[PDB]
Length: 261
Length: 259
Ligand SMILES: O=S1(=O)NCN(C2CC2)c2cc(CCc3ccc4c(c3)N(C3CC3)CNS4(=O)=O)ccc21
Ligand SMILES: [Cl-]
Ligand SMILES: [Cl-]
Ligand SMILES: [Cl-]
Ligand SMILES: [Cl-]
Ligand SMILES: [Cl-]
Ligand SMILES: [Cl-]
Image (cartoon, rainbow over all chains, first blue to last red; front, top):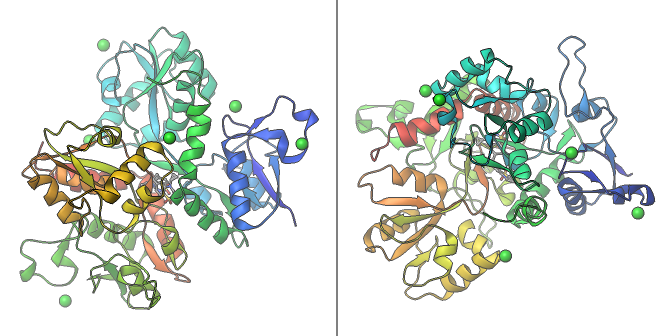
């Protein structure tokens, strides 16, 4: 009766230990969600096996085939019992799996190369010298496409037509583009990743301004799962004990490479 | 039948309209949670009656009688169908009712009278000239009592023995104490209330420093309610539509008095 946990290789949530081939089972992995999985299992009284999602994806429903991919797909098609990963709580996912209460907060944020004269989305929207963009697919692009807020609508009208294209295929390319564009590119991405990169060498990026929306990561279990209630309560217990803040500090700042300000 | 909504008179969530005595039913009330109730009702397809919780409390279990008071009590004992209020998501409440996903974020924050040389909890912890405290019961006090974080442990060690007492019986008293202590008291309270008061005349308070923890308000229904799932999805839809942010800006900043 070992619980099958699906998760995803994304730093600092789940990472392969360099000597993983000499280790076995859950010991092959380390990270924020590795620690969280252990805490959840302890407070719910189950043993578990960590597995990495087969297709490396989070969870989206292909509009044509109507098939779920990623960790959500592994839940609804019965390949895993629970997903413990940086999986954003969204309406479409909530329809098909049960999300625990959030274990981490996040929102759209701005990444600049140190020295860029930008403090806010409003700053971005009122100037043209500094290009800015998003991942070419996903929720951040759609946030701007759909927004009725004047500043964000102005940003969307700019980004949708900017040339050369301000959209990037991957988060890594957005980050690289900030680092290599000599201050002439700002990247819009989730605050959690932005904060993580701010603590990575070469320590040349910064998160600026407040978050543009409010989201969270949640643990996912299939509907009717015998684990759902206990996991949900475990998340709240961990927060009230300060352990979620403790874990984020550990993996973002204690293990950071750029010191303080 | 008509859905019975229990809520609480707390500005700006639910307030009596100025002319409420001329009005009946749901029209007597205005505020963030009045607007949220209408949106939830619309997206879940029910009609509803707003009611103010009889005992004026949020929801706690008496350790001796084991009886739940407040809005949580009204749900578990069958007096109301749903609570739409600034009800903090907590473990012990989640054990007895169903919380929707959070519809507003909040965390512990610091309120000062403008001019007080305090910018952070760390600032508070290093001195005693400016007294500081919390509500005398509830989660903010317990956050400090239980913290193993050095700065917060230092603050607790001060607050627990400070004389005269730095604890207050009500949130209103904490706010009033800030305003009336001539710059010598700072109050630890939820960021949402701190932000609200900062936008109210006489515009003499300020929110300073980052939040000390991360919580949220949730809508509550009794376990097994036919409304739970629909309400939960409705909160996420409203968030993804930007409507929760729009409503907060409406009631905190558009209707603010301090520029
Ligand atoms: O997509 S949501 O579910 N819906 C919409 N919103 C917006 C407010 C409207 C949010 C906002 C957040 C951040 C604030 C928040 C709320 C509740 C809790 C939090 C953190 N924690 C903390 C560890 C992070 C623990 N458990 S908890 O008590 O439930 C997360 C998820 C969502
Ligand atoms: Cl990675
Ligand atoms: Cl091993
Ligand atoms: Cl310019
Ligand atoms: Cl606007
Ligand atoms: Cl009436
Ligand atoms: Cl510490």
